[PDB]
Length: 166
Image (cartoon, rainbow, N blue to C red; front, side, top):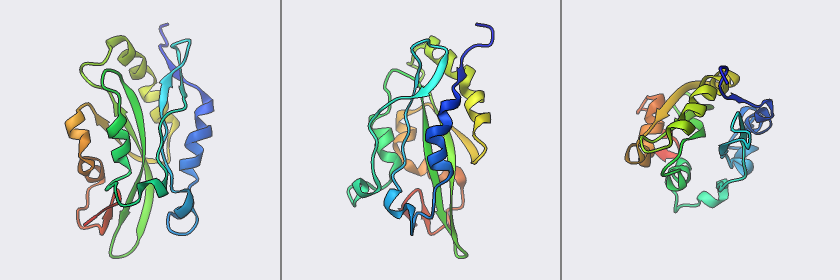
């Protein structure tokens, strides 16, 4: 109780996929699909990944400007959750990919649920090191625009950002 809620080690199972991703151009180009939904465990004391709606690189096609759009499209309306996105960017020198842990929690979400997430907020954050930076979100309108997420990394000069071209 005092320790609050923590995150299960089983998380590495899904996080490892994103962490050990191959070039998005050559190998991952086909498996570029990236999405993970975290939910509260039955005991309400453990954080695990549950089966949820995810999108594939192929699914992106041309109808979707940014992959993160899917998440903000079906994101929770009255609940808190975590979002995992592969930060991608391109520069005059070269392009690289990384991971960013996103904390999603609306002001209308349950406080009790929020408290549990807060407890594992640092647990999951510390559990992930492949990440470059952490981005917190709490606005549907603010998250609606992928520009904010991509801009999180900064560098508008980059040729590519979150899949959105310059």
